[PDB]
Each structure stands twice: as C-alpha cells, then as structure tokens.
Amino acid sequence: GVTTFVALYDYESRTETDLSFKKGERLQIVNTEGDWWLAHSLTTGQTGYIPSNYVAPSD
C-alpha cells in the first residue's frame, strides 16, 4: 500500500540514484528493507533513494 514519511532535515543529492528533498516534504515508498529506500516526493515529483534516518512516518 501507500507508505509515507515526512522529511525532518534537508538532504542534497550526492549520488546518481539518490533523491534530494527539503525538510517538510512528503515522501512515499516506491519497500522499507535496509536503511536506503526508493522514494517519490509528493512535493517535487522526483524519485530516488532516501536515507531513512532523515524522515519520520506521516499518514
């Protein structure tokens, strides 16, 4: 189903496959195995891996 999170801190992309996001952005999982999750930003529409320790669950 839908699994959503909100960013606690800004994160700037630094790899070919990660996703930049700002604090307060809503991000959804495209599963949650490991510590890097393939996500989609509901703000920007962009996608990529995000660090799970920058986000918190958001219904």
Image (cartoon, rainbow, N blue to C red):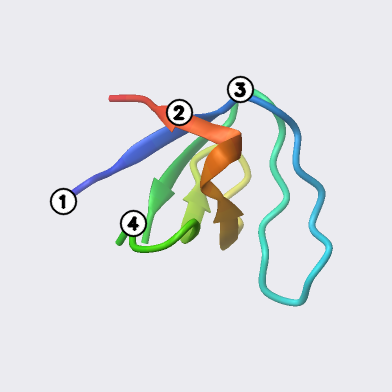
Q: Crowding at label 2, few (<14), some or many (≥20) Cα neighbours within 10 Å?
A: some
In the image, residue 41 above or below residue 59: below
- Which residue has dot 4 on it? 32
* Lower position in the chain sequence, tag 2 or tag 1: 1
Nearer the observer: mark 4 or 3; the answer is: 4
Q: In the picture provided, is 37 more to the left or to the right than 21?
A: left
Place of residue 13 in the rendered image (x, y in percent of width and height, measured from the top left): 79, 57
Mark 2 vs mark 3: give the one in front. 2
* Rendered image: mark on residue 24: 3
Q: Amino acid at mark 4?
A: Thr
Q: CA distance from mark 2 to mark 4?
A: 12 Å
Q: Name the residue carrying label 1.
A: 1
Precedes in sequence: disc 4 or disc 1: 1
Amino acid beneath label 3: Gly
In whole angstroms, how far apart are the C-alphas of marks 1 and 3? 22 Å
Helix, strand, or loop for circle 2?
Answer: strand
What is the spatial separation of the Cα atoms under label 2 and label 3, in whole angstroms? 10 Å
Judging by the rendered image, the residue that carries numbered circle 2 is 56
State the count of labels. 4
Query: Earlier along the polypeptide chain: callout 2 or callout 3?
Result: 3
Q: Residue at x 28, y 43 (%)?
A: 3
Q: Position of residue 28 (x, y in %)?
A: 40, 46
Point 15% across, 51% down: residue:
1
Mark-to-mark CA distance, 4 and 1: 12 Å
Residue farthest to the bottom?
A: 16
Image position of 26 (left or right of 24):
left
- The residue lying toward the viewer, choosing from 52 and 5, is 52
Q: Residue at x 33, y 56 (%)?
A: 32
Q: Is residue 39 left or right of residue 4?
A: right
Of callouts 4 and 3, the N-terminal one? 3
SS at mark 3? loop
Residue 38, percent from left and from top = 47, 63
